[PDB]
């Protein structure tokens, strides 16, 4: 939407040759999360993640790549890769949507990410693409 995000999307394709649906800026963690089409994540990363390294050089921020999906469960699984997600649950009331992910006894480790880093990525992405304003790992 913004011009900044518009710039990021343009440089992403310029370096990788892959089209980014969106670029979720995360100033707090000096990070940029690029959303790409299904099956495209490997092309965007490159051999030895060389393209990730060039994007960091190019945009001066940390770079992350996630495959987008209009299906909440799908993108949720993409958002928490090294995790066993049993069930996802979305509750809405007065237009307030909250997602509750059910991960096994101790999958809560990778789920949260060092310093919420991971679950914040979930919140940011689900907030921008699904109107979800609350995420909960249970």
Image (cartoon, grey):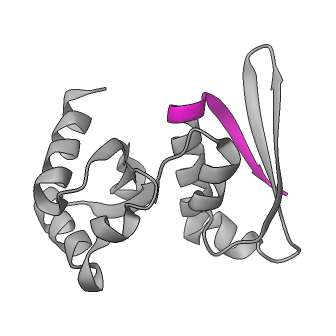
The magenta region covers: 128-138
* Residue 136 is inside the magenta segment: yes
From what the image shows, is residue 52 above or below residue 20? Answer: below
Please give the name of the residue rendered at 52% of the width and 34% of the height, measured from the top-left corner. 129
Q: Is residue 38 left or right of residue 60?
A: right
Pinpoint residue 14: horizontal percent, then vertical percent.
Answer: 11, 53
Q: Residue furthest bottom?
A: 48
Q: Residue furthest right?
A: 105
Please give the name of the residue rendered at 26% of the width and 75% of the height, measured from the top-left corner. 46
**Quadrant of the snapshot with the C terminus:** bottom right
The part of the image, by quadrant, that contains residue 95 is top right
Please give the name of the residue rendered at 19% of the width and 64% of the height, measured from the top-left corner. 55
The part of the image, by quadrant, that contains residue 132 is top right
The part of the image, by quadrant, that contains residue 133 is top right
* Residue 93 is inside the magenta segment: no
Please give the name of the residue rendered at 32% of the width and 63% of the height, measured from the top-left corner. 63
Pinpoint residue 90: horizontal percent, then vertical percent.
Answer: 80, 36
Q: Is residue 108 left or right of residue 72?
A: right
Q: Nearer the viewer, residue 122 or 86?
A: 86
From what the image shows, is residue 97 above or below residue 59? Answer: above
Pinpoint residue 94: horizontal percent, then vertical percent.
Answer: 79, 13
From what the image shows, is residue 96 above or below residue 115? Answer: above
Pinpoint residue 22: horizontal percent, then vertical percent.
Answer: 35, 41
Q: Residue furthest top?
A: 94
């Amino acid at each position: 939407i913004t011009l900044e995000e518009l710039r990021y999307i343009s440089v992403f394709h310029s370096i990788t040759g892959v089209t980014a649906y969106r670029c979720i800026v995360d100033e707090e963690n000096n990070r940029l999360i690029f959303l790409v089409s299904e099956g495209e994540a490997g092309r965007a990363i490159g051999r030895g993640g060389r393209l990730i390294k060039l994007l960091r050089e190019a945009l001066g921020k940390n770079i992350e790549v996630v495959e987008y999906s209009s299906d909440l469960e799908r993108i949720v699984k993409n958002l928490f890769p090294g995790v066993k997600i049993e069930s996802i649950n979305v509750r809405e009331r007065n237009g307030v949507k909250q997602v509750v992910i059910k991960v096994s006894e101790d999958d809560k480790g990778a789920a949260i990410g060092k310093g919420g880093k991971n679950v914040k990525r979930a919140r940011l992405v689900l907030s921008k693409l699904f109107g979800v304003e609350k995420v909960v790992i249970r």
